[PDB]
């Protein structure tokens, strides 16, 4: 019937149009209440209990703010109430494809369980969306509020996942290209999804967010750029945009890639791999799926949430004993032990195809110290983390259009040297973390020696504590002294 | 083993002594990660995703702050490091006995499932604590850090639940009476547990907390009162104490007793009642328990969390169909419908023994109006809520001892009229909410006519929207205009 | 000329229309940068350095928010861009008449310096506004943006001060009556001025505000009430409105009437009285005024700010020696000493005409304790403070119109008993503070005996520390024992 | 005399020892209430009304936190209550030397008025401190609380200004070296002064601070480094330390060097230069000083505050007409106009001795565009701003000592490549801003052409809006295209 108000600690009072309420009040959407935003991060940062549900509300709210702000200041863009609703829906729905513990599922579990498939949460969001619509009779409701389902469903999916295949989009024409830059911005990654998570994650983690999305919204305008209408920021704000990506990188370094968070995600992934043959999830027509195959049936995937963790933990079946035991070690805080971190030097870049060979390389190192235990490849975990500004080696600010106060309809470019010499020289790097599955004192001492020796042999950077954890190894390396 | 630092969004960096870490890193404590602080409140306030776990860390931290502050200002009290740890442990552990959805479990479910038993979360905390200690070899660890288990375990339990029965306590002597006022203050309810939840619940709900616990700590002292050493507040702070209880009452009104939060707790309770025969929880020695009997075995209770909700929702067994269908209605937001609220007038006080008769009474009202449908007792839910300042009809500030700047060791009393005439004249009241299980438009119209007629017949207060929802009924009542 | 953005810590990014910018960029408006919001409160709460200038920006902003919100939800009201600008201007300009140290000037100094005149900051705001307009060529600028100066200048003044004398207003007709409720709400005091100062004063004082003005704005509507269009709140929000006035009262008790803040305001007022014959302020046509007569000439008043305080403090003229010495005692923190506080009982209400007799009464009390020193009337200060809900004895919520969800265009009333029995039974009271100008130990002891005896003789409430500060006096009073 | 509590919106309840209260309650300290922390920043960011007084309380509080934290963790350091108080005093007093509008006084005015003198606010703080102590009888009070004035006064001054002339300090010996790193850290700039102004300035400006000083305090330890006991940070925190300096730089870029804030500081400085021959400030024995010579007499300098601004503005003396007129233009917002910003390229570094030649260079540029007006050197202002990490070209993190969890007493170093490749390559740069004193449309157009042509001639970076403001000039430069 009518609009609803929701109170959110980040944004305050969010108004929801009744079509949005109908999308929200479904099993496919409400499911997001049972998926933690930060996965294993809650086990390090106890405030991070938030789930994808409330993040999705915030993304939909902000998407609506930005589109409304553009419309109000530039009526000549002809943004319709239909446009506004479609953008809010895409915003609400771009997290629907997340799986248990969020990035651990698409980032660790599925790549190990189903190495042959190419799955992303984005693709999952489109499939869940289609399933949500079809299972809940949403198309008639959309027509009731003036949407045109064929066009608008296409538009919504395109906002989430990009072109479903010269202007490549079918949901809207080039004169509305700027609409595609709101929810998931494939050109430079500046979108309302980051703005909600910066604010929400900081609130919960107890870390402070430096980025002012409202200021940015106020200074945003649409300008013509190479025969597209694109969103442009005020020239002055270029520093704040660099700062936005800097904040993204700090949040990754301190929280999202926390070394213990990551190892908890890894352990949970391992328990899931060991339980995968025994857990059954009933999908369409009563067919049974596994944790690794629920992504093939949306009805099964609907029922795949963080509950899988507790189902395993609370199980009594002897078949689940191995999985259950890994989870029990998490509760007792008997975790795989962090050994250290290093980075490649020079132009060395570690390729994905080499990842599996790394633990073997570490166990093959020949440190000169007397060791009571010997460790094997299987005792080591090597995590390779690609840290960047969202576009691999590229500077995303080279893909942003700006305008000046004296000519607000004229788009310009601003280069790095026009801003500051104190900015980063590079935009991507790799971090390598090593952990040991043997947690006793002697094994850990040994693991350290192998680790630092491997760093030396590969010409990686000297670990920060290298001289303390491996004082007999670090003197060999001239470049470190 | 050394101290750990945890970052909490409410309190910042909390330091945890290694004994505390050992208590925390157990299944019995980690269980609290899977129990929402506010139960069905998350279904109204989407920021309220927090669980009892992080609340318990905060209660333990604040307990430590208060005891440390007292010791530092008054060395003559002889507060030992042992005392400090025992108070931190009680603080950490006073939420261990909570069940699924927190107050819904002890407040709605158990009273209906096991009407013959007298269960409280406090009692449950003592039992889970004992089980935690015993199952994890904590006593030797306590001795390692200078605790004396026999005395100190007793002291901890007493802080949580009160005397395990003229000085009634055995864990500490009258010399240390003030220590019993920190974690769970039976005398007037001013304790660190409230202070954490005020700040934490407000952070998550998106409502602002007006109470300054750090100011109160700074102004607190121990003074002799009737041959006990008790905590006294500075005279000046009496207004801020009344404001504390006022804030508690606002939080209940706006959030904890939100009409839709309460109906969701009621629907979930109903699903639990319908599933209770079929859900099995394995406890000690492989014995099986139900949701309603897990409270009799701590090993089973350890595994009784919010996960029960999803286990039901995801079930395929036809035996669980009824329970599962209620939960499905929650997801679709097809909830029982709020009809209205009223209060008794005069000295009328509704007794617990009469609660069951109320839906009958409503259905027996004879509104003088044309009705398409007739409703029966079973179509109505009547919720009676007792709102007070924590001590029934009493003013808790009558039970607080104060001191003056001119004589800091002399305790005094301050009465209501010494403070302000703008304070409440009563400290307890009752609210009556009525809901209808028939949700269609005609049933709801009818429910409104019965409801308002019943209010008129009983001489209850006029519902705020009475003239709008029942314009043909409200004219009959002279007292209402 | 285009819009400007200002960043405010309370409201974020505030957009200012160019007409508003022109009003702001005048000596009459910028003057507010040199008048502390809380006067002598900065000398107790060191974060309270804020001035009337930034408060005025915030009031203008919120005035705009509320009027825009109403227009967007109810287009049928025909709120024009002209209406919006007039309301923003009134909001911006309702503080223009404040004098040095804000309420100290109109509340203490002018009543003692010019007892024959009836001066308010509201009257001063109208005069300064007229002077601002005329001195800066604003009328042509107003016309340029579609305002009609004769009607609209009237309207703005009426919003600030009320009718400049059946519909009593000339700036707008009855169908726009709701516009008069925004900036300065004479009917019940619920206006945007309070909302900005609650948030701003809390931010600076270091106290937390619990009123959510944004929620209130979202729930506000215009409805017909007795043939006027008035602003109505949603029924549900009635609790929050009581809480609003409760917050106002707490802020007055903790901050705005802090006993030391008030004594500093008194000492400053005293210095101003002693300097008044000697300070010259040049006004229109070179005429000279005094501090007490600058209110008669807006050109002189433009130059009358907190700077008077420093002019006196830094003076070398022997004529200002007495004034300067009082200010020097403030810097050394040699302040008059607080003796205690009490309240009248029963029907007793202390009239303004009796205020001067009260120190005489205190010095006339006859304690019957042995005293080293005797004190005279001139050694005592007695401060009488009227605390209420903004309408003397009346409940302002009786003057608020509400609507219900089922009939949003139908206004209703809600009485106290329809809300809660835990609300105040009275809405006004008086506090009496007593201070001694003799600050030595023996004088202060004596002052305490006189004070408490005077309380006993007048049947005032027992001071909270009475038994400690005057143990030989309090036993005499049966009613206190 | 007992402790006082002050409530601060940044830190909460700060306890002040009575010796500190005595230092605070003097004309020399209370003077800081009348000096804005951010000077002309209040004229851009209206929330920035805060003064140096409340900043100084915060620096003293944090200095006490850090020293107390070190003592509690490491009793073997033998930090005494005497050490604690001396560090709190130095913290309280390190802002005493600030002049009107803070950095504008020492940063713009004194360098132009007294080019021969080398004045810093640091030197001024030492002088004011000595004068504060002597004028107010503080030495006996210090002895009363166990301080030893000769040693401890030396120690305090050394903390503020560095060695008053191998261990160069006399106030404390090398085993207490770490105490010198708290208030003003000459080695790397990581001190409690930054930490307070980050949090306080952000709170007031409406920008969010992302540095967590409390976390840093908790991780700090004293370790031996080259036969000194120095403060060491945990290795892990190195990222956060880089982020701290990054935050400092953002605050300078967005706020402290705001182009309009700076121009206001310049205009005020200009008014002060024009008033300097006519304003009189009475110092010791009735002698008169000027604004530029008050720094030579502490009794005069005590009375030199932001009041000087209003004294000029409110003056009637025809000798002050020129000064008064500049201030009046500030009120009307007729400010000098910003033309643009650029930076040097390559190894070009602009020296202080060249600053005065720059406007001449700009006016000598030869654009070869048709110009209606010609501009002269005196029409241009050129502001050169040095932005760095506090140590000119150096990386301050190269001057930080760290420790590892496995060996907490063993200090180590961490290099930039051990941390991240996404860090800055350089640590100092210069910004050049140009403004025009002729504010009309034709002058401003011309100014732009000269500016951009000058950039091209000097091989400076292309202004961001260069192509829009000077489309005929920017094509000439190949390097820009
Ligand atoms: N800040 C704040 N939030 C509130 C308060 N009361 C409820 N909420 C939150 C919970 C929800 O997220 C949102 C809306 O709840 P309401 O109680 O207004 O809506 P509800 O649908 O129960 O009422 P309605 O259908 O309009 O009668 O506001 C309040 O007093 N303050
Ligand atoms: N505020 C804040 N909290 C952090 C940051 N890094 C981690 N935390 C949180 C996560 C935890 O709740 C707590 C301690 O985490 P740490 O990373 O310091 O401890 P962890 O045990 O991983 O390191 P350690 O064993 O000392 O090497 O602080 C940070 O950069 N800022
Ligand atoms: N939150 C935030 N506020 C800022 C920042 N930069 C400036 N402000 C504040 C200062 C003012 O209150 C307001 C507008 O400042 P701007 O620098 O955008 O306006 P200005 O008139 O100087 O620039 P313009 O005339 O548009 O070139 O925003 C920023 O980076 N973050
Ligand atoms: N947060 C908070 N701050 C307060 C309150 N009352 C006063 N303050 C602030 C003002 C000052 O910065 C500081 C100390 O104020 P007090 O009223 O406790 O000190 P005062 O010296 O007036 O009392 P005393 O001499 O001890 O009777 O706390 C309050 O209720 N809450």
Image (spheres, coloured by chain):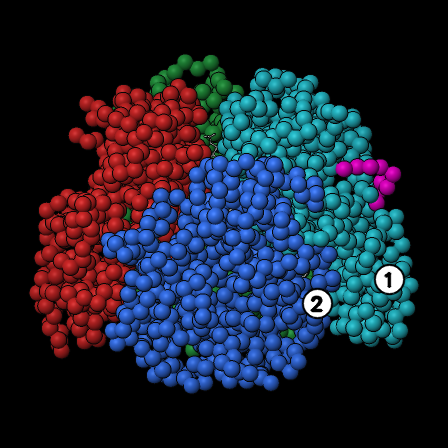
Chain colours: A green, B cyan, C blue, D red
Q: Main secondary structure of the magenta part?
A: loop
Magenta stretch contains residue B118 = yes
Q: Is mark 1 within 8 Å of ligand 1?
A: no
Left or right of B350 on screen, residue C139: left
The residue range painted magenta reads B112-120
Does C232 sit above or below residue A328? below
Position of residue D435 measured from the top left corner of the image (x, y, whole percent): 20, 64
Which residue is at a point 25% across and 41% down the rendered structure image?
Answer: D128
Count of numbered labels shown in the rendering: 2
Task: Name the residue beneath numbered marker 2.
Answer: C414
Q: Nearer the viewer, residue B341 or D118?
A: D118
Task: Name the residue beneath numbered marker 1.
Answer: B458
Position of residue D260 measured from the top left corner of the image (x, y, whole percent): 27, 61
Which residue is at a point 55% across and 41% down the rendered structure image?
Answer: C449
Q: Nearer the viewer, residue C331 or A435?
A: C331
Which residue is at a point 67% across and 71% down the rendered structure image?
Answer: C403
> Which chain hosts label 1?
B
Left or right of D414 on screen, residue B30: right
Q: Residues within 10 Å of mark 1 (few under 14, many from 20)?
A: few
Question: Disc 1 vs disc 2: Cβ atoms closer than 8 Å?
Answer: no
Does A371 sit above or below residue D281? above
> Which chain hosts label 2?
C
In the rendered view of the protein, which quadrant contains the N terminus of chain A?
Answer: bottom right
Q: Is mark 2 within 8 Å of ligand 1?
A: no
Query: Is the residue at mark 1 from the same chain as the one at mark 2?
Result: no
Asked if residue D347 can be seen in this view, the reply is yes
Q: Quadrant of residue D265?
A: bottom left
Q: Secondary structure at mark 2?
A: loop
**Residue D418 has which mark?**
none
Asked if residue C8 can be seen in this view, the reply is no
Does A230 sit above or below residue A357? below
Magenta stretch contains residue D164 = no
């Amino acid at each position: 019937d009518t609009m609803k108000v929701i109170n959110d600690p980040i944004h305050g009072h969010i108004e929801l149009h009744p079509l949005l309420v109908r999308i929200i009040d479904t099993p496919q959407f409400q499911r997001l209440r049972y998926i933690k935003q930060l996965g294993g991060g809650y086990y390090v940062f106890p405030g991070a209990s938030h789930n994808r549900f409330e993040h999705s509300l915030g993304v939909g709210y902000l998407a609506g703010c930005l589109v409304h702000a553009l419309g109000e200041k530039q009526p000549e863009l002809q943004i319709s109430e239909r446009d506004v609703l479609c953008v809010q829906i895409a915003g609400l729905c771009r997290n629907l494809g997340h799986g248990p513990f969020s990035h651990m599922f698409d980032g660790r579990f599925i790549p190990l369980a189903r190495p042959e498939v190419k799955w992303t949460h984005e693709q999952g969001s489109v499939m869940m969306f289609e399933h949500l619509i079809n299972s809940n009779g949403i198309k008639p409701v959309m027509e009731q509020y003036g949407l045109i389902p064929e066009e608008d469903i296409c538009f919504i999916k395109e906002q989430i996942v990009g072109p479903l295949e010269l202007w490549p989009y079918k949901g809207r024409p080039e004169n509305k290209s700027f609409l595609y830059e709101i929810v998931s911005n494939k050109r430079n990654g500046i979108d309302v999804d980051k703005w909600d998570y910066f604010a929400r994650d900081c609130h919960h983690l107890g870390i402070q967010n430096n980025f002012d999305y409202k200021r940015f919204i106020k200074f945003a305008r649409v300008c013509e750029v190479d025969n597209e209408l694109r969103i442009c920021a005020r020239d002055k704000e270029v520093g704040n945009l660099y700062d936005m990506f800097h904040t993204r990188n700090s949040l990754h370094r301190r929280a999202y890639q926390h070394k213990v968070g990551n190892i908890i995600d890894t352990m949970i992934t391992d328990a899931f791999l060991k339980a995968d043959d025994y857990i059954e999830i009933t999908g369409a027509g009563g067919k049974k799926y596994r944790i690794s195959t629920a992504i093939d049936d949306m009805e099964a995937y609907t029922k795949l949430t963080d509950n899988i963790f507790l189902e395993i933990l609370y199980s009594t079946d002897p078949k689940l004993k191995d999985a259950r035991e890994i989870l029990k070690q998490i509760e007792y805080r008997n975790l795989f032990k962090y050994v250290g971190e290093t980075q490649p030097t020079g132009q060395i870049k570690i390729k994905r195809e080499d990842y599996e060979s790394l633990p073997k390389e570490v166990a093959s190192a020949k440190p000169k110290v007397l060791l009571d235990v010997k460790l094997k490849a299987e005792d080591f975990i090597v995590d390779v983390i690609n840290m960047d500004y969202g576009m691999q080696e590229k500077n995303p600010i080279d893909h942003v259009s700006f305008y000046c106060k004296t000519a607000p309809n004229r788009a310009i470019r601003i280069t790095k040297n026009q801003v500051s010499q104190l900015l980063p020289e590079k935009f991507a790097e790799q971090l390598i973390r090593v952990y040991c599955k043997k947690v006793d004192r002697k094994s850990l001492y040994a693991a350290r020696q192998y680790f630092v020796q491997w760093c030396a042999d590969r010409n990686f950077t000297k670990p920060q504590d290298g001289d303390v954890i491996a004082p007999l190894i670090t003197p060999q390396k001239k470049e470190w002294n």
